[PDB]
Length: 107
Ligand SMILES: C=C[C@H]1CN(Cc2ccccn2)C(=O)[C@@H]2CCC[C@H]1N2[S@@](=N)(=O)c1cc(Cl)cc(Cl)c1
Image (tube, rainbow, N blue to C red):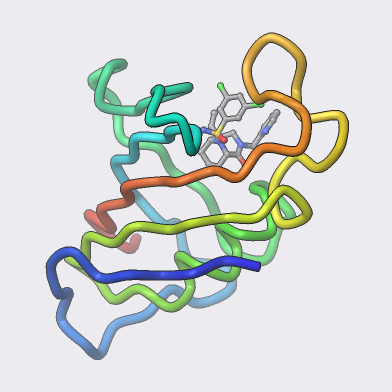
């Protein structure tokens, strides 16, 4: 599944809803601690819309429980991410993913 551990609190009241655009910065790492991808490296916040099947399940479920402003660590099992195949070249097979996610804005 996905575990959400708060790093720093959000507003405690404004949570993502279907149809809203979620704006984040994230860093993704393997259990080894090695980074596989970061929006901060690209100088560009990552945006997705909730309920449009745009992201892995662990994101859909994990970010939905964050409030605006919150920074959290999401630990995501392979079955809530890229599963047995992974994504060759980027995400290894059967990988547990750990993301540092900061919910910057809802728009
Ligand atoms: C590039 C941004 C997304 C990519 N996706 C959706 C997605 C889109 C196309 C292919 C694989 N996965 C995602 O579901 C997740 C979670 C949100 C932040 C990023 N990833 S990601 N960091 O695991 C990632 C995974 C992969 Cl296979 C490629 C890249 Cl460029 C990024």
